Length: 149
Length: 149
Ligand SMILES: O=C1C(=O)N(Cc2ccc3c(c2C(=O)O)OCCO3)c2ccc(Br)cc21
Ligand SMILES: O=C1C(=O)N(Cc2ccc3c(c2C(=O)O)OCCO3)c2ccc(Br)cc21
Ligand SMILES: O=C1C(=O)N(Cc2ccc3c(c2C(=O)O)OCCO3)c2ccc(Br)cc21
Ligand SMILES: O=C1C(=O)N(Cc2ccc3c(c2C(=O)O)OCCO3)c2ccc(Br)cc21
View 1 (cartoon, helix red, strand yellow):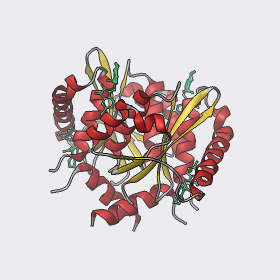
View 2 (cartoon, rainbow over the protein chains, first blue to last red):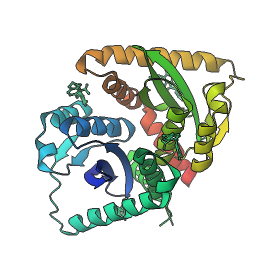
View 3 (cartoon, protein in one colour):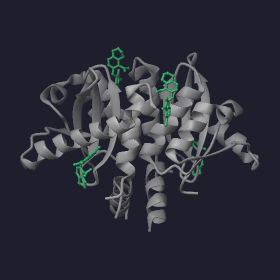
View 4 (cartoon, rainbow over the protein chains, first blue to last red):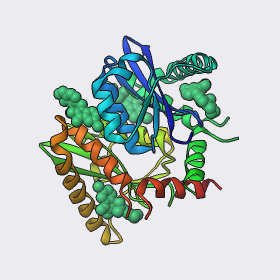
């Protein structure tokens, strides 16, 4: 569980926000892309796995699960690519709720920046620092550190 | 010192590689940009501070130290902006040594990817996972987790 992440793709302002969620902590990383392609997904996963110990990725849809570039990047980075099928049905809803919450945050900061990509990174910042009392950033670090010991 | 980072800018293939090093661990994040402007630097710092608890950054030169956009981002993200003058002279050399090693890694993977930005991210991955036996990615997580408790 410390190495498990879920991909999520959501849409805003005619663009795509790609999100990776660290399932046990709720910590996220995100980027704005013009469209979700295998190549963009593969590059996002290489960035993520260079930053955190990514063991398994639950992919967000079958096109990315199938994509040969995604599979090349998972092989390169040592990642086990799995489906993201919500076998525990509370999954569809957790992700939907996360997308809702992110977009709400983006709307709270949207006026402070011109580019959507800046507002998305502000929202990443606010989500990961929010006290829930630990934050997601604190949880992911404690989870992986406990794992290291 | 768990919250201290150093920015570093280096050049390759007529492009700029912007690097943030977590001083205590050697862990890095990096990006390729066409040129090192305040706006790119500010955006890079926002991304970094949304992913790790960045308390202080030693900026890589006086133009970023001065940049009003950089200072706006440091204010937004709660980051103390400092100079990066090597008062400990071994700093000039440690950074030079890092740039040399990164470029070496890049040259080792350069042929596996078409875009420079992909090879840079492969090199981030190899650097942060290399055991020297803890890796930089392991050190940074242990350092911050110790700090959390
Ligand atoms: O509200 C949520 C949520 O459900 N999460 C996902 C999530 C998944 C698993 C978890 C989570 C979260 C989370 O609440 O962030 O928290 C405790 C650990 O288990 C979010 C992630 C980003 C953003 Br913006 C909002 C949210
Ligand atoms: O709000 C902004 C912002 O406007 N940018 C920088 C910026 C400066 C000038 C611009 C910008 C942006 C931007 O939104 O990226 O959009 C193009 C027009 O001119 C930020 C970078 C980091 C952080 Br925190 C906040 C911001
Ligand atoms: O060779 C180095 C180095 O000196 N570091 C920077 C650094 C700074 C401070 C440290 C470092 C390192 C490090 O070796 O990464 O190691 C232990 C903690 O103290 C590098 C970072 C990335 C890459 Br690619 C190469 C290197
Ligand atoms: O080696 C590549 C690669 O070529 N890319 C993907 C890629 C696919 C097709 C392309 C690419 C790239 C790329 O280098 O980004 O360049 C444009 C030409 O067509 C990678 C993404 C993640 C990871 Br790991 C490795 C790679």
